[PDB]
Structures are given as C-alpha cells and as structure tokens.
Image (cartoon, coloured by chain):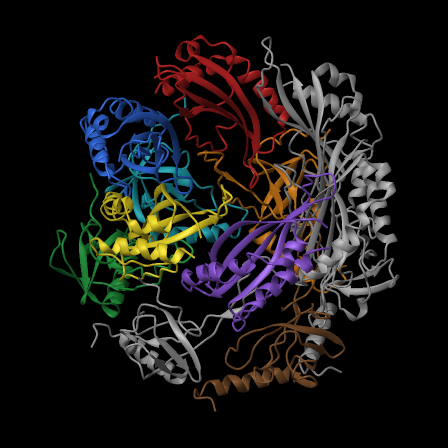
Chain colours: A blue, B yellow, C purple, F red, G brown, J green, K orange, L cyan
Amino acid sequence: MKHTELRAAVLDALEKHDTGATFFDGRPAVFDEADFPAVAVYLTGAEYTGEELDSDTWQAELHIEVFLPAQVPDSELDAWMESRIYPVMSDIPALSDLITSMVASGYDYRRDDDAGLWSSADLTYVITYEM
Amino acid sequence: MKHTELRAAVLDALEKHDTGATFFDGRPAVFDEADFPAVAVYLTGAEYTGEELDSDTWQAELHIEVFLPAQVPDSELDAWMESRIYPVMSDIPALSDLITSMVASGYDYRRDDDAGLWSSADLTYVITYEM
Amino acid sequence: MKHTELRAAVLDALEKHDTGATFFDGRPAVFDEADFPAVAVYLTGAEYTGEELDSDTWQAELHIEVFLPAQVPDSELDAWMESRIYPVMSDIPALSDLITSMVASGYDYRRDDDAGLWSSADLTYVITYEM
Amino acid sequence: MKHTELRAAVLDALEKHDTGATFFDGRPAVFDEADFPAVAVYLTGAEYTGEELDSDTWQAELHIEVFLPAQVPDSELDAWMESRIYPVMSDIPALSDLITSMVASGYDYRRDDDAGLWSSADLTYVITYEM
Amino acid sequence: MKHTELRAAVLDALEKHDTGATFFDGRPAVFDEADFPAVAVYLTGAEYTGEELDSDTWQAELHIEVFLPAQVPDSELDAWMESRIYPVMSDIPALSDLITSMVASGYDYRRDDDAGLWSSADLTYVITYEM
Amino acid sequence: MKHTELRAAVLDALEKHDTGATFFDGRPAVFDEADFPAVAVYLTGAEYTGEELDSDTWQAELHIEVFLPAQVPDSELDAWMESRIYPVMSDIPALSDLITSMVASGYDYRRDDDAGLWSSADLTYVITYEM
Amino acid sequence: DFDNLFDAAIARADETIRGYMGTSATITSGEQSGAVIRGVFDDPENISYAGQGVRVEGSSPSLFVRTDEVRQLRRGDTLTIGEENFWVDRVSPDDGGSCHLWLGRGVPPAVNRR
Amino acid sequence: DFDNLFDAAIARADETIRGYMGTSATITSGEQSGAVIRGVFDDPENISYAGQGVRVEGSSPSLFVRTDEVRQLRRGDTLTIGEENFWVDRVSPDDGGSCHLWLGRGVPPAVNRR
Amino acid sequence: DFDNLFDAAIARADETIRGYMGTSATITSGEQSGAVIRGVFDDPENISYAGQGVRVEGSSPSLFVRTDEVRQLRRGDTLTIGEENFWVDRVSPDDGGSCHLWLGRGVPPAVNRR
Amino acid sequence: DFDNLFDAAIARADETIRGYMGTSATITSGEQSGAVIRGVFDDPENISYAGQGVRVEGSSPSLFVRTDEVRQLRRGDTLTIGEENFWVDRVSPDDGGSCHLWLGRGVPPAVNRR
Amino acid sequence: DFDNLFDAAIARADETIRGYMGTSATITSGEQSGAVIRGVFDDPENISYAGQGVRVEGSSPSLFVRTDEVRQLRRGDTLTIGEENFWVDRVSPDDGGSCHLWLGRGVPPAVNRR
Amino acid sequence: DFDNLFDAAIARADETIRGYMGTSATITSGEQSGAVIRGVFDDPENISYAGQGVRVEGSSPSLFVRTDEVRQLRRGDTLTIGEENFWVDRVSPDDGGSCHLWLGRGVPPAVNRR
C-alpha cells in the first residue's frame, strides 16, 4: 500500500548522508562478500487495530537491519546505529506526512554462530498508519 | 453449510477483477512451475462462541494466500495484495448476505528458505457466521 | 461407567442415517487402503470439575475424526461435517438421557504432510456427565 | 515415610478386590511380554503449600496407571479404570486416616506410537498430607 | 558469595549424622561407579528482590541432590530423603544465623532413561539472605 | 549509543582493581587456552520505556560474563564474584555520570555440557540512560 | 507367466531362500484356517520407556512369505510358529515375489470395528 | 542427435533396463487415452500414525517412464498396471533419458482448480 | 534337528566363536545356581551428564550367551565374571542360535514386585 | 602455469568431462551477451510443502562450468541451453578448476538493489 | 594366562601398535609418582560457543595406554608428554587389552570432594 | 628424531603432499613478516540465511600448513595467497606433522582485547 513509498522515503532519508553501505530495499537481500556492511528495510505485522470509528487506522512494524562481517566488535555496530541510523530518521517530514504516529520499539544484536558469515544489528520501530 | 458458497463467492469476486493468476480453491493446491503466482482461499478455526440464545453464531478465520516465485521483492508483493486482494472485500453483497460480521485481523509474509521455491503472503480475516 | 454407552449410542445414531463409511469405534483405528473414508469416535480429558456438592460432575471431550483419501479438496470435508454428522447428532435423545449437558467446542482440519496418506478432519464436543 | 505406607495401603486396597493383574510398586517396573496388563502406583510433586501456620501440610499427586497389550481398544481400559480403580479408590479407611483430604484430578490415555508394545492409561489424584 | 560458607555449614551439619555416602560439594560432581549413592549441595537464582529499603536482601535457591544407582525403587528414595536430609536440616543454628529466612519449596525425582546409570532425588529450598 | 563509553568506563574501573584476567570488551571473545579465566562485558535489550515526555529514557541490560576452567568447582566462581565484580562496581562515579538508574537483576552459572571446555558465570544488571 | 524375464529369476531366488532357511508354520483361523506355509521367521529387539521409565522390552516378529499363499488373510487371524502362537498385524505390499508378514503375540486384541 | 556421446549411452541403458525389467501399462483418459508405456514399477511401503494410534499403512507406487512418451500428461489422467487402476500424481523432470512417475491409487481426487 | 539347513551352520559358527573367544562364567543364585556358561563378554563405555556437570561415566556389560543353557534365567539373580560379579537385567530373544545378556554391576536393586 | 604439478591434471580432467558429458549453453544478457559455454547440466528434484498441502514441486538446475568463462557474470543475467531459458542465481567459488553454476528459471525477479 | 586364545593375539597387537606409533609419557604425582609408560597420543580439535558468540577452541587429548600400568591412577594426578603437562580426567574401562586415557591440560581443578 | 618409527613416515608423506599438492603462500604482517610456506589451500562454500531470505553465501578457506614454520603465528596477522589477501582466524592443533590454518578474508576485524 504505502509500504513501497514509505520504504522509498526512508531509504532516501537514509542515503542523504555519506555513502559507504548498500541500501537494500525490502527483503530478498543476497549479499555475498562484496556488498558488505549494508542496511535492509522491511515491514511486518500490519493488523487491524481500529482505535476509532473513522477509518481502519492500521499499524505495522518496521525493521531496519545493518549487516557487518563476522566477528567485527560491537563497537562498530554501536557507532553505526548511533551515527548512521538513529539520529538521521528522528525527523523526516516525508514519513510524518505518510504515517500518523511514530514510536521506537527496540534495538538488538544477532549473529551467525555456525561459520559466522555475518553479524546484524536490528532496529525495530512501530508505525501507526492510515491505509 | 456455508463454507462452500462463501469460498465460491469470494473466489468469483476475485476473478471478476483483472485476471492473470491461478485461483486455486480449497486446500490441496499443488502448483508446479506452470500455474505460478496464484491465490488460494480457505477457512480455519470455526468454534462455538454462542454469545446469544438465538443461534449458534459460530466464527472462523479466512485465509487468502497469494504465492509468488522465490525472491521477488516484497514491494511487488505489496503491490499485488493492494491491486488484487485488499480493496475487493470493501463491499461484496454476497458475503454480507452469507455471513453476519466480517473484520480484518492480519496480513503477513513468509517464504521457503530451503530450496526457496515459493514466497507467500497471507490475509487473515475474522468472520462471524451462522449456519 | 458411561464411555462405552456414550460411544455405542453415538455410533448407533450415526449409523441410523444412510451408510457409506466405516464407523470405527474406540481408538486403535488401523485403516489400510480398503476401509477408507471412515469416522472414529473417542473421548479425552475427563477431569473432576465439581461445581456442586451433590456428585462428581465430571467433564470430558468427544472427538469425531473423519478420514478421506490423501489430498481430496476440503469441500467434501465441509459437506461431511455440515451435512452428515452435525445435523444428525444435533438432537439424539439417548445422549440427552446419558449426558447432563452438551456443548460444541471446535471443528478443524489436518492433512498428512509426509507421504500424504490421508486427510483427517476433527469435530470436538464437550461433555458434562455424572457417573 | 508416609509415601511408603500410602503406596502399601493403596496396593492392599487394590489387591483385596479380585486380582488378575500385577501390582508393580514404585517406578522402575520393567515388564517383558509375560507380566502384562498391570497397574503401577507412584507419587509426584510434593511441594510446600502452607495452608496453615501450625503444620507444613504438604501436597503431592498420586498416579495409578495401568498398561495393556499394545493396541488393545479403549473399551477394556474404560472397563478397567471405572470398575477396578475408581470404585475401589472411592473409600478406603487406611488412606483416610493417613492423609488429610483426598481429591481426584485427572484420567487420561496414551500409547506407544513407535514399536507399540503397550497402551497405558493414567489416573491421578491430589493428596494433601502432613509429615 | 557467602554461598561457600553456607554450603560448608549445611554440608557439615548433614555430615554429622550417619555416614554411608559421598558428600560432594558444589558443581562438578563426577561420580563414577565407586562413590555411589551420594549427596550434592549447590545454589541457583540469586537475584535482587529488594522488599526492604535498608539493604540488598537478596534471595536464592538451594538444591540438595541425592544420587542412587539406576533402578532402585523410589520407596528407598523416600526412606533416604526422610532420614538423611529433610529431618536433619529442620533446625541448624549455623544456617539460621547465616541466612534470614528458610522456607521449603519442593522435592521431586528424576532418573536416567537412556543408558540409565543414575537416579536422583532433588530437594529445593528457598533462601532469603543478606549480603 | 553511549554503550561504547559505558563499556569503556566500567572496564577501566574493573581494570583499576588488581588484575589477573583478560578484560574482553564487547562480545567477539575468542579465548583459546591461553587468555583463560577472564571477564567479558557487553550490552543487550535497549527498549523505549518512555515514562516521561522530557527525554527518551531508554533502558538496557549489562552482561558481565566471567569464564573459568572447564569443570572448576563453583567455589572459585563464588569467590570471583564476591571479590572481583560485585564489590568493585558498587560505587563508580563515571557510571553515575553516564547513566541515571542502575539496579542489580541477576547472577547465574552455566558450564559447557558437551566437551566441557569452559564454565561461565553471569552478572546481569539493569540500566537506564538517555541518548 | 511373468512378462519380465527377471521376475522369474527373483521368484526362483525367493523359493530358494525360503526353502534354505526359516522353518515352516501353520495357520489357525482365517479363510486359510488349517494350512502350512514355509517362511523365514526373525525377531529383533524393541524397547520403550513410557513414563519416567517403564521399560517394556519386547519383540517384532517377521516372516517374509511369498505373496500367493497369504492372500485373503485380513488381520484378525492367528498363526503358530510350531509351538508358539502369533497373530498377523500387518501385511506388507508385494515387492514382486514376496511380502513381509508382521506378527504380534498372543490373542489378537478384540476387533473394535463397529 | 545430442551433443552428448554419453546421454546416448544412458538412453541405450534406459531402453535395455526397461526392456529387461518392469511391465507394460495402459494409460487411461488424458490426452494420450489408449496407449502402452513400458516401465519398471515398485510399491514401497509407508505408514502414518496421525492421532493416538491411527495407522494408515499404504504404498507409494512408481513406474519410471521414459521421458518422450509421457509429455503432455498433466496429473488428472489415470493409468492401468495390468488389471489394477492407478492415477498419476506427480511427474519428475528428466534426468537425461527418463523420469520417475509418481502414482496414486483409485479415482483421482476431484480437480479443485476454480 | 531343525528344518533349517542354515540354523545348524550358524549354531556351529557361534559355538566355534564361543570356544575361540570369550571366557567362562560361574553363575550364582537363581534356579541355575552353580553352573558354568561360556560367552564373549564386552564392556562398552557410556557417559551420562544428568545436570550441568554430573558425569556418571560407567559401562554396559554384555556376554552373548547361548539360549539353550540359559533358559529360565529370570532377572533378579546375579552371576560372576571371572572374580567379580554382575547381575543380569535383560535377556534378548534368540536370534536363531543364541542371545545377548545385558548385565548390571553389584547387588541387584531390590525386587519391587508387589 | 599452474604452480602445483597437480592442477594441470585436474584441469585436463575438467576439460575431458566437460567435452565428454553435458551440453553447450548460449548466454543472453550480461556483459558476455552472445557467447557459448560448455557445461554439464543437471536438474535434481526439490519439493516444498509450505502449509498442509501446498506442494510446489520444482527443480534445482546446475551446470558446473569452468572458472575462466564464468568470470564477471554477476547474478542478474539470463542464459539458455538448447531451447530452454534459465537465469543464474548463485555462482559457487572455484574448487580449483571449475565451479558449480546455480540456475533459476524464467525471468530473474527484479533487482531490488536500492 | 588369558583363557581365550584370542586375547593373546590382541595383547600382542596392542604391544606392537604401542611400540610402533606410541610415545613415552612420565606420570607425576599420584601413587605411581615417577613412572614411565608408552601410549599413542592424539589431540582432536573441538569448539564451543558460550552465548551469542564465544569461540573457545580447545583440544581433547587421548593416550591409549595398556590397562596393567594404568591401574590405581585415580583422577587427581598428572602426567607429562615430553615437555607438555596434562592431567588424567577420565579412564576408560578395559576393552580387552588396553583402555583409552582421557587427558586434560594444566593444573587439575581443585578436588571439591567434601 | 622422534620416538616414533611412524611420525617420520607421516612427515615424509606430509612433505610429499605439500610439494605435489599446494601453493606458495606468502605472509605479511605478524612476527613472521615476510615469509613463504607451501600450503594446500581449499575454499569450501557455505551459506547462511539469517532472516526471511538474507543469503550471505561465502567461502571458508583453509591452507593445511606445517606446524614448525607457523609457530607463534597468532591470529591478528594477515596472509597472502598469491594475489589474494586473507587473514588467519584460528590455528588447529598439530595432528603430528602439520595443522589446518583456518583463513578469513579482507582486513581482520579490530582486536577488541582491552
């Protein structure tokens, strides 16, 4: 619905700064050891919390995952989502017009254990949007 | 018995719009690489929430499955579900005749990881019906 | 004890209508590919909800399984549980004499995943009985 | 310990009624295909519910569970536990003196899926007792 | 922690009774088929429930494991645990000084199915201790 | 976030006390049997407990892992966290500057089951901070 | 008879093996009733633990008899390996020249059909 | 015929094994309708348990067709092995000279396509 | 003696291995009481962990007796390998000429029958 | 050229098996565009079930091309063998003288790069 | 000495293999204290992950000494393979002529007996 | 040189395989700095999936280096296979004559030790 344009707007607002990372839209990914540390944006959930007898007022969940190689220390990830992600999206008017209300949900770490080919930091947001 | 006419009505409503997809009704599916991106429709749950001493007034969940090949970007899946599925149940007289109340519950994504043949999107609808 | 009498009465009520399927009573089942689509009746649970200081007033769950060839479409299964078993057992005097209270619980499906030998459908009732 | 005399007394109550089965006390059991259908009695739980400030008043669970040949139908199990166990366990003075309050909890079935040598039906009471 | 001195005190107090067992302290255990039926004492939990604005007032849980060979009947397990552990610690002044409040929590059995060299009985106590 | 700064501050405070172990910041670790028994410090959680419309007021959890030889008795672990971690951080002004509220959460053990190559003890701490 | 020029070989081999090992047996009850079949009996182990442990060590007899004789057995019928008594539980589908007969022990448990 | 020098050998091998092994078969319905395919048929034994004990022991037949004759077959059509009636469920892709045919039993289940 | 032509050979073979391998064993207790059984004893090594570290490493002795001389052995009675005593726990059914004997160690644990 | 005295043997081996089995392939799209590569194509089965019954039976094509030609193919381009069209999904790393080439089917799905 | 006629052969074989592949080893502490034995040493690799990621690479040494010398070794005492210092953790039971010796590394961790 | 009679043979074989099957690795950085080894390198292919589909296909190189020339190699230092730049991750323990060098790719990630 608006997921395509919401993702486009958020990736554009992410790309305004200096480059140095791939900006994989959506989800299929397929990285290989040449397009490394990168960022992927996608959505989940999207249920029918009504909350008002005026419109559907749906709500979904935003995932932005940044991938760095293998056993790179978590200081690099900390720097990444303190400099490249968290402040840059804090005020984007395009998303403000596209969605109703924005609120942070969580931010965690995961990694490959067997063969350790990757290490991801996930930032998870909650979107209330009128679709 | 209302399941068969409900499935037939929703399937006919889906087919009335632009074609271009297989419309596998029921359950067993069986796709092969010829009948690709397709839509299936089925029911689950159907317990006995009485709520009134006038009729059984059961309620169940309707799944609209849509299947796309392998790693087609989820933007195209969003486009498919918006241009093909979601708006059509905005107002269908046959369903309003058949069932009592119909509300949305969810809309999710999933896919095959091993051998990655398929990628599916699910529309979950809550239906209160009396039979 | 009431389990044997309950099963006998319900199987007799089922066989009262026109036949066309096996009426396996009990538990062991064992089908082979000649005794197909069949119906089995059994009991589960049997807790000791007191609810009144005059008798034990136990309650349990009655399961009616129906088994169909492999991956037949669910339309015939819907027909089987909304035109073959639900209406006939909706009012059976013998159970009313035997059982204090009869309430519907659920109606679900399940298909054999590996090797797909069967497609089974479950119809589950709840029983408040005193013995 | 009261567990030993509880097991001895319930075993005596079971054996006083017409015999015809083994009465393996405890837990290790071990059967072979000569000591078949047989009943075992044991205890589980045994926490420290207070229930009063003068005595510890512990409570545990009593399992009386019987084993019958492989895929024997449930009819003989229903004949067993509601004619040989439940009527017997209705009132025995020794247990009444030994324990404080006696309440039945549940009565369920199970069988060996793989191999399939046995079919065991369990029957559990809850004991409130003071050590 | 003070766990070392607590374990030493309880181990010495329970050692003062009749011998005839090994008194493994702490975690590693390692039995072999020569130091058999034995008792181990250890601790788990130890979070920061405050419940008083004067000190940390931590609380943890104490396990008393007792190991017997293979398929010994649980009757002698009860005899062991009602002769070597449960009565002996009911009043030990050293532990009373060392900890604040002593409350029993549970007492259960476990046994080895595969291979089956051991059978353990667990005594779980709860401790509120200030440190 | 300030996770790098907080980790550096707590690690420097720990190193100020008498050394004797490796001081792994972050989480990649990689020990081998030469940098053995050691301590690692890392962060998890980082949700958005708002609690007031004046700051983000995020909160997270601090893991202090300590690794000891294989099946070393837990007495050494108790001594370690009664002498090396729990007392030393009880009052550090740098953390008080960096964060707002800091409360103990838990303290647990776990050893390697298969191949038994290590034994870890975890100090879990709760922290609130603004970004 | 067999339009394969290979199933004849496998049938001859099956006859040879059945005659070279596995003794004989006779049937009680069933449409065959009194009859004698030559097979190859075997009995492996099988252990189950049920509860915390209730080890019920048993056996799973098998016969591997040729398919022609064991037609119209159904399941409730019994059989004797000489002195000892078993009962047919499952009949394997024909592999081309024979089938595996799975047997229980003692009296077959009820019928519980209707 | 093929830029192979090897698939020719495997094709001759497939022809010779299907000649030396397996039976003929008469396809029924479908676009082929009356036609005879020579294959090698096997019936492995497979059992499911479902609920508590609900053993549904059955077989999973296969015939191992040659690739050429089975084109435009789809799945709804049926077939006859000698005197017994099967129906094809799945057709494998060619491995170079042949493809396994997965068989059902009895009447094919509906169509359920619209 | 047996309608076998093959079980006689395997009986000869197992007796040959028992005479060529394994030791003798003096059985005590049970109905057999004092007797000497020849068989091949082995002690596979098995470890259980119970909790986190509760390693209870031990062995699972076996002896591979011949069924005929060891019938009605039951379970409770013990036996002596060389100079140190085990106790039987399970008796496998005969595979055609003999069976495996599983043994414990030390005094058998109670009876717990009634 | 090959500083191993062994990689020459494996290179001759790969050349022999590629010229002895498999077919030629005309690559379309990509920087190579019109070019013919000799490889060994195979299409193993793969079955996925998704839900209860959603069987989506397919295939997993592979080619096993030598490493020199497969250089700078990326992933987006397509390919055709004989008359049928595929598209490369993944390129295996060199094993010394070649690398398996993993093929999809039909049009490659978008790019979704930025 | 061995009443088997086979354990003599296995003992000769064990002596031969220990002499042809083994290495010397000097046990220290324990009741043996200063003593020298011979055994085939090996050091397999093993990895573990203690959380989101903690790579603890280690080795699992083994020695395979004959059972006669390994008697009354207990577990606390230690041993030197040339210069390297290990400590026995577990002693495998007799397999007929020898037993594997499971080795640790560094100082044995406490005793923690009582 | 060794109380072996066997490890000498395995060392000769190790040298033979290194000469006949291997590459001239050149090392930069670390205490060894500029040095040359003859190690047989292989690149097995491994893929992870992470989320929905996040395939991160890559390789896990290995070198099979001889222990004597690669002592005190540590982990942080890098390596060069001809024109390609790798970095060692972990060093396997000696199996008797050599060890497997597990290799990474690109710049080693930080040190993160203080």
User: Considering the image in quadrants, where does the N terminus of chain B appear?
Assistant: bottom left
**Which residue is pictured at 64% across the width and 78% down the height?**
G40
| F43 horizontally vs J15: left or right | right
C116 above or below F131? Answer: below
User: Does the image show residue A56?
Assistant: yes
User: Does the image show residue L42?
Assistant: no
| B82 horizontally vs K4: left or right | left
Q: How far across and how far down the image is residue A110, in percent?
A: 39, 34
Please state which of residues G67 and C9 is positioned toward the viewer in this rendering.
C9
Please state which of residues B16 and B100 is positioned toward the viewer in this rendering.
B100
Please state which of residues F63 and K32 is positioned toward the viewer in this rendering.
F63
Task: Give the image quarter of residue G57.
Answer: bottom right
L98 above or below C85? Answer: above
Please state which of residues C55 and A68 is positioned toward the viewer in this rendering.
C55
Residue at the outermost bottom position = G1
Task: Give the image quarter of residue B37.
Answer: bottom left
Q: How far across and how far down the image is residue C110, in percent?
A: 47, 56
Residue at the outermost front position = B54
| G82 horizontally vs B26: left or right | right
Q: How far across and how far down the image is residue J86, in percent?
A: 22, 59
**Which residue is pictured at 31% across the width and 30% down the height?**
A127
Q: How far across and how far down the image is residue B111, in percent?
A: 34, 48
